[PDB]
Amino acid sequence: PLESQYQVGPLLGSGGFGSVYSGIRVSDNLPVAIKHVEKDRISDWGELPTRVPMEVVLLKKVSSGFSGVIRLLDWFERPDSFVLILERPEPVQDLFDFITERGALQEELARSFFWQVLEAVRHCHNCGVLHRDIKDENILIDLNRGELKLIDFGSGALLKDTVYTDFDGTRVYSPPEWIRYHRYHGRSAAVWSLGILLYDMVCGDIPFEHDEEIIGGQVFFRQRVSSECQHLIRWCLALRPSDRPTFEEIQNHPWMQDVLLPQETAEIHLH
Amino acid sequence: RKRRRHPSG
Ligand SMILES: Cn1c2c(c3ccc(Cl)cc31)[C@@H](C#N)C1(CCNCC1)NC2=O
Ligand SMILES: [Cl-]
Image (cartoon, rainbow over all chains, first blue to last red; front, side, top):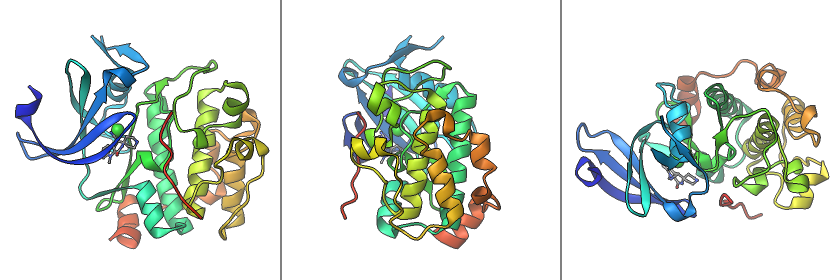
């Protein structure tokens, strides 16, 4: 029974998805997030080996001691909703707010964060899960540990090698082949969103707002950024999906060398 | 220049 086992606190966020609250598991005072997903706005459903949101299937698949992805601790069904209990880092800030407050990130910091996001996304893909909504709003920073956590699997799918013709993630992080053709492959679309994310980190906002910008093929740098970083970004944002790097090629890029440890990142940049 | 969130969908 949900209401007996968690003490509900303040609302943390709400939107199309539903509403998420701060909570504490009464058992051991563990910080949690309590996410209410209305059944009306659930598009994709799966089956665990009952009928659940696809979000729950994907979360169960990536669930692990690895801290780069949010851990689903439990879930409950109600008449008109599902309630998802997620681990909550404390103290925490999302990457959207962090970038808004701090502006364009130093490259050392962006390298550490981007590397951690890569490792998180590789974890998802290794577990058979395509996220489909990689963005700064869907990344939490454990401020004490300097560890990033990928959240919000509400637009995800099972990973496959064929074309996707559906998409409900964030349009400004979506690739030109989706904008033009309503078609994309999972990995190359993911790399496109990672390009957008990296630009966002080093310039302080995303490069494109409009469809014509997304398909136009020009990346203008509004901030002073190293040539090596520009090169990686522009590779991730190649118009042709087959011109984009693999995850291996990203992590082997010269800009990606000599990453800080999470603990070093916290000490130098967060504490 | 205005930075904003972009809801999914
Ligand atoms: C503040 N917050 C939010 C989310 C959180 C998940 C865990 C924790 Cl610790 C905090 C969270 C997401 C949800 N629901 C999303 C869901 C929508 N996209 C951003 C993340 N919304 C949040 O507001
Ligand atoms: Cl979430």
